[PDB]
Amino acid sequence: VSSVIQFGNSLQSVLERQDNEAMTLLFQQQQQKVLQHTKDIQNNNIQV
Amino acid sequence: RANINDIKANYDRREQEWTLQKNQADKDAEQLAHQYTSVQEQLNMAQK
């Protein structure tokens, strides 16, 4: 039962790092999109 | 005859002044076209 409790703790750690990696990867993708629309803003700022 | 010459000379001077005012109004229109283009590209930048 001590072995079962140890691998339950390991499963909880892996299972929260998986969701944190999903959140981090989504944030990286959407910041990569925002930093392109900001480049479009700076493209119009030189036409002005 | 000298009075006739002075009347006609004043007519020539105000023709020259009209030419100056017409040219300055054309230059003001050529300014305001580009300033309209600037404000329209500011509108495109805000709309992005």
Image (spheres, coloured by chain):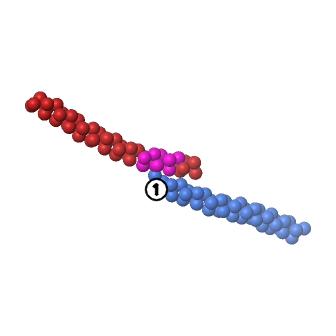
Picture residue at 24% right of the left edge, 38% below the top: B15
Residue B2 sits in quarter: top left
Q: Is residue B26 magenta?
A: no
Residue A21 sits in quarter: bottom right
Q: Is residue A41 above or below residue B36?
A: below
Picture residue at 75% right of the left edge, 62% below the top: A19
- Judge left or right: residue A33 versus residue B20: right
Task: Name the residue that disc number 1 marks.
Answer: A46
Q: Is residue B17 above or below residue B35?
A: above
- Judge left or right: residue B42 versus residue B11: right
Instruction: Tell me the amino acid under the disc marked 1.
Output: Ile
Q: Secondary structure at mark 1?
A: helix
Can residue A24 be seen in the rendering of this structure? Answer: no
The residue furthest top is B3
Crowding around mark 1 (Cα neighbors within 10 Å: few <14, some 14 to 19, many 20+) is few
Q: Position of residue A6 (x, y in %)?
A: 83, 68
* Chain in red (letter): B
Picture residue at 76% right of the left edge, 65% below the top: A18
> B43 or A13: nearer the eye?
B43
Identify the hue of chain A.
blue
Q: Main secondary structure of the magenta part?
A: helix
> B19 or A9: nearer the eye?
B19
Residue B21 sits in quarter: top left
> B43 or A5: nearer the eye?
B43
Residue stretch in magenta:
B33-43
The residue furthest front is B1
Can residue A25 be seen in the rendering of this structure? Answer: yes
Q: Is residue B39 magenta?
A: yes
Picture residue at 46% right of the left edge, 49% below the top: B37
